[PDB]
Length: 291
Length: 292
Image (tube, rainbow over all chains, first blue to last red; front, side):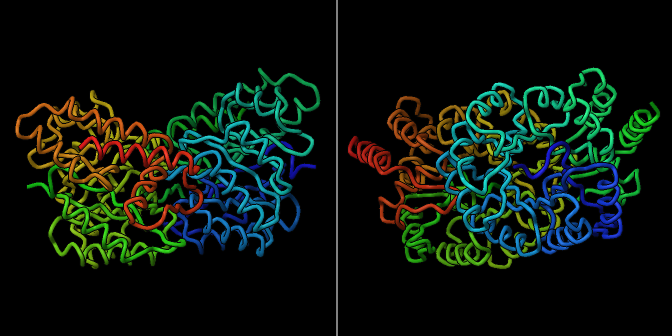
């Protein structure tokens, strides 16, 4: 079947004075579960994984796993641009209790399509746990071509794709090529959801659900039931345009902190929004909530 | 005032049965020095730094430094998308004796221009060695804006830019803003050197100079003496076209192994060329050499 359907949260990392704050992470995760998140996706870029130490990643994953306590799937981002290191992080995540792992394509080194297959399959064979492929060309400069998706979807452990392609010709080429009964397609881009849902996607792995999980999941449920969400989505679109102001997770963290999850901090090389922009974004959020 | 001028080599890592071949590293570095390479850039993408263990990176850089023995600068690629990590690798590089560090912009996470300054300067302040900034939007998806390049050149230890934008309006905008007498502009794209040299660049940091260092440096020496290199470049251009068959360093290692620097191996996620393509590529090298 599927790991989940609807909204997964690309969970942010709460910092206090540059330290991971466990009490706040616990509080955030519980807030997510209570507000209908269908999965917690851990240590992705939204969590700033490129600057987390291996230890922090481990502390964060175990905390999430143990708190969530089997309530929804916990999906650990473990792939990096190094295949051996990816195998090892994946193996360790399995041992900690992850329900699944998520593997970005290589980046910075990149690789070719045949090299992708080798890489993804090496890790999936080693770990034998559901694998969510992650394709985001605006951060990797490479893609998982549709024919590469069919090949990979044929692997018994590789069951899903987070597609932040934001390219609807590519989604259509992928659907023609897989079986959604057993291979799920999740948008990696909050603001394409109305069309992504309408085109047969299984849900979304979401930034904005870090702070509006209830209304984002409720948007999914509405259309799944047969309703039109094109207009319903607008007030959310307005909030998403405000979030456009800088590279994720620089803006979203202004909102997680605003809700009391960590201070407003980002680890170098990221930097927090300046005062003016922080205030505007928070106000745009308050405005969404009143309505 | 520059670290070097002309051709620096983005050094490739020699693997034999998936292990760094130290004697081949040594033989290769002497080959480069003897064919007038002007600098050696260690542990970059061309060296497959993303798949090297911390141990390997360090054995590789210690070998190069001790062998080069201060003959040309040895510039350690140390930057990564991770500031803190980048600082510690850079302090370790200095302690092994590197002359300069190279610091690509962040990638995957990326950052904005303001954060770029904080990233590069925090490393620059902490290591206190000459820094070469490296901008390669086709692998990072971000850029160091000309006005950002300007700001960073004020920094005491930021002395150069390896520029792989392959964008000449960009180049001219950066020239307008910095002083090339004290801030060097090195191309990072082997195939634009003819234009890069006519527009006042200080050299190149090169992939193909892994195997034809003598020719590639002589091409620079030629235009520098006031000779036109446009036509003289073509045979080199022909070889580079053949090198674009796949993603660096996948093709170049088909040629370094060919010259006996390691076997033709790449660490996953990269894979070697199919050996049919490996054959075409080697013959094309051979054809370049025979033309001589």
